[PDB]
Amino acid sequence: VDFDNLKTMTYEVTDRVARITFNRPEKGNAIVADTPLELSALVERADLDPDVHVILVSGRGEGFCAGFDPYEGTVLSGKTQALNHLPDEPWDPMVDYQMMSRFVRGFASLMHCDKPTVVKIHGYCVAGGTDIALHADQVIAAADAKIGYPPMRVWGVPAAGLWAHRLGDQRAKRLLFTGDCITGAQAAEWGLAVEAPDPADLDARTERLVERIAAMPVNQLIMAKLACNTALLNQGVATSQMVSTVFDGIARHTPEGHAFVATAREHGFREAVRRRDEPMGDHGRRASDV
Amino acid sequence: PVDFDNLKTMTYEVTDRVARITFNRPEKGNAIVADTPLELSALVERADLDPDVHVILVSGRGEGFCAGFDPYEGTVLSGKTQALNHLPDEPWDPMVDYQMMSRFVRGFASLMHCDKPTVVKIHGYCVAGGTDIALHADQVIAAADAKIGYPPMRVWGVPAAGLWAHRLGDQRAKRLLFTGDCITGAQAAEWGLAVEAPDPADLDARTERLVERIAAMPVNQLIMAKLACNTALLNQGVATSQMVSTVFDGIARHTPEGHAFVATAREHGFREAVRRRDEPMGDHGRRASDV
Image 1: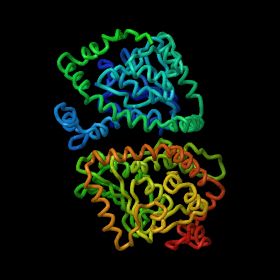
Image 2: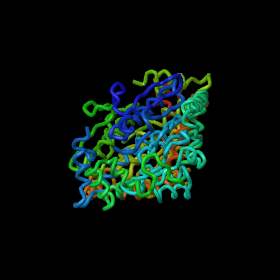
Image 3: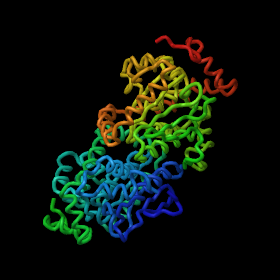
Image 4: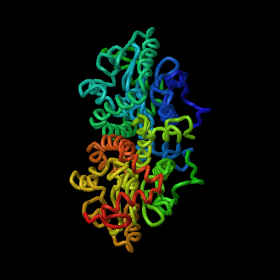
């Protein structure tokens, strides 16, 4: 990673806030190969800077993140991975796991890093976008944001494996058994988000939150996060994550997975998504009425 | 950033399906320096991504495996920030220390969390910070006469990796950590710290045999076996043991006792400081602790 030629996001430190800001708004800040690498590198940079006390992750454009979009001679090559997605030959789930687990590993830097992480969600945080967002220590969301994992319906299982740890069993299952999304307001109500300001107030309340955190000594902040993370990680997060990443690979290789891909190839991915969600009445920015 | 054409602390070679990572500071007991965890972590990742590699074999050159611990400018890891944080007569900052020592342990933990099997071969000694590395490996094979343990429990460390109780169980971990005593490789096999403990003349051959039997399996099978076994391992609270133990190691280095050890090492050299620590306990150098 080259801090002078970042491809997917920007880095800027203002006062004590390290702002990591997705920079592909034309693509909904969709996750590409470089996203986890840049995210993890920038988080480490922030961790090591004694003038940084808090990391604020956000996206440009209409929403936080819409989800998923030098490796030659590795298991991660484009050729190896595309061969592993052919339907009419046995695939290798561990070749898939080596690829997908490294996305998740990059995203997990927001959980495991020394310093506090805040994610600001506006608009949408769906599918892969939640594999990032749910790792953050604090999530603040616009009241009218759309948040969930629609590809439970076809083509994914949340690789991060964090829904049960963030929502509890009942509410995680409510979303993962349907692919339904909740509003930012409901995310606050269910405790997925710490607050849900009206969209006109989101930036102001977000800046207030990070300022308050940033006013604290780094040593205190690091200790609080270490203390709290002993309880979080003791819930079996590592296991939830591993098995969910395997499951996501499975979702991308079932008959249902391949039929979705074939639809995306014929009509484009946006239209494949519309046809997935339309029978459920929550296509686009429509609410799921949870 | 690690340069595979200019490695500082260790070497890398793939022979058939075995990625050999071999420590390369033989006359300093392969002592751990800043680049050690960076190189180990990068080379383990490279092995993981190479479809021609099935197993990773870590060993050290010289008389023993590892004797333990020996671009950051403007970071919490700078030489100046860390040196300042070790002054005795001012308040120190345990989180400045944690940021440093946790990143050593993170590099070492790549042997545990990587996709593929890891094997550590111990000859001679694996003591102190050496064990922070070794105990992360999936398989440990040791010369019957090797010396294995954490002598700085006596003064100046607490095992930052935090793995002793996970690898030995409560009673045998406490037996070594309440004393700083070392066990032989033979005892390590009996206690299940090592999977076998060949005579030193047979160590290399038995090691090669073990890694070849592992390498004869498909990569997909191996990765699944490791993932399955690690769910139980990690469910023991390894992450918490490692975090609290890394905090405790910082403390050990900043107590009156820790400062007195460093003052002796600074005045007379580390070797003499170790002499004074271990000779009263009858186990200085390659002597056994008679556990």
